Image (cartoon, chains in turn blue, red):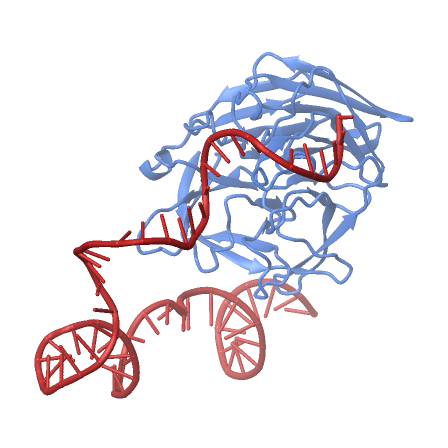
Length: 351
DNA sequence: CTGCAGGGTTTTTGTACAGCCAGACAGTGGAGTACTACCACTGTGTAAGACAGGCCAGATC
């Protein structure tokens, strides 16, 4: 456990509070640029490199067959691991564009070719969903399961704008939790089914979901109806058996009370959770370790690194997982005159 | 019940005697009155982003 400050070298104004780090093939790719894509980088996606403290961002370039992506702020990222057919995929869905509307379109991102000289080409394919599509939402979670042997995706949670009946230009910008029904989406084709279960009373948002061996564990979300941060741990068990993806669920005793956590994989299935917030006012400071197996989730409090007074007295903080026991955290910075660099950056490393 | 029509009711609308004050009219000689034009000149316009060229640094045979 260690932390080092990073110097936000030029072009650090493209990092916004909500954003994603897609970790694929060595270097990781920042995504969710602030504002619309400026023609300095007409794609919108960036490759990030951390070297001797310098955080340098390079402009990736799409391939010829790709449809282009609007910089969603807080979408649902699902890492589809390397296997047949085209490894490895990242499922982005659905978030909200730089104009405040919700996308409701599933995108699949893959790698194409390299280099020559330290260059990587990507490709984004928008994939149609026939249904019974899930309603446009943001903050939810999507997870990838492999069940004998078909790959499916489980989609759950997330806020949404009010339905188009009570929607009023005085209550326009208000959000309410989407109804709690789990959507099972096939990677191919776009046939999506929707199931409901009694144990899931209300939906959640910003809840870290972990998925392994046809089982999905949901940690504590933030329910906006009762304003509670439930410490219940949720588990659901699905199996795709022709012709239904039959789904069941169970409640567990203890689940951590964190919302919007930074889940970095370190081991085979062991994760380190950095956490966003314990309560509405007081953010989480402790770092936790969550291993998981067929038995269940195993929790362990590990020693958190000594925080600088700044990151300890920060009101809000965000970030993502660079992977391999490394994570990136950001602190909004106050000063006059404008720094102008708004976000000061830290790199945290496990072992 | 409706409609209109002589007259009633009380109330207005005005003209009628008849005496009498308050302000406009004329004016003036000019004053100071009061209202207009003329004169240069002001403020609100206020930061990043696109593109072409040169070059260097790291990866490859």
